[PDB]
Image (cartoon, rainbow over all chains, first blue to last red; front, side, top):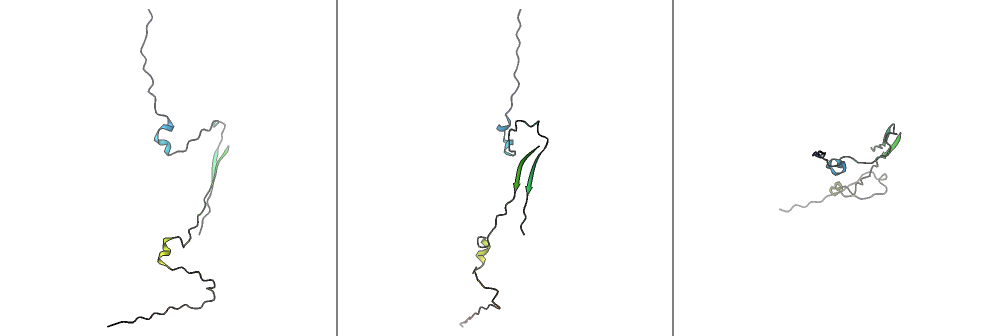
Length: 49
Length: 49
């Protein structure tokens, strides 16, 4: 006698680009980030008098 | 490791003649101000009775 069961699905959630939190961050898809050691940003601020 | 951004300030000049502070003044260009010793403006006020 073959028996069947009832399974309920995993409740899916709104993705990251579809929330309003991404208005605070700038999103890029860096494909190979496990190869990166460091990443730097360099500012150069000239100051008037 | 990676360079991700190389950023720098640019100081935009603000001319005196395009501030609204110059509304309270009268601006005349005077080519040779080093020649002048002293300026002078003379008033004549008549008073009726």
